[PDB]
Image (spheres, rainbow, N blue to C red):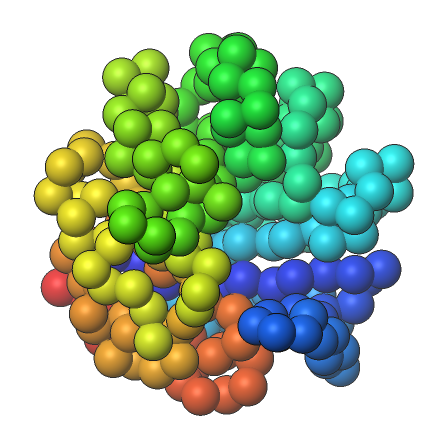
Length: 229
């Protein structure tokens, strides 16, 4: 299991969207490029970037900043943000982005997702699934495990699975893992301390950590150390 430090960007600014009853925006002082180099210098080997500006309106995707980030960062950069076209994905991988996160269309259009998968390969493509517990885990009507079953048999390797109720939902991941042992799970949501990281050790291939690193709850060094085998 590896830590994956994350930054959410709006108009070149590092922010975070706190969620719950009211979506609230907190703007940080950090320069995105400087913060990412710092994470890298601390030992991060994977970085996650969410373009919230592009996620809100694809015409205003932050290509210029993403491009620059991709070519100064010497480790793997992964990018997400309402990405829903092959052109988008191809533009991003051309900037030097290692992996692109798709997912808003995982069910409204399974054929395009498959197409993206075949064209660019399973190592370059991550499927984002937001999932909730009703009587069963469903995608936010369809069963999560069945949606996973479908993509798993078509060479899907990477998923970014978020419980949108959230510490972390350890039970959710232990059992995705129990059933789909070959899927590389990235956990996200609810990471509040080192203990969340420890509880996911051996279960998830990656843990997305944003707020905790930004607010100084723990450091990249501490995260890497406690995930070390």
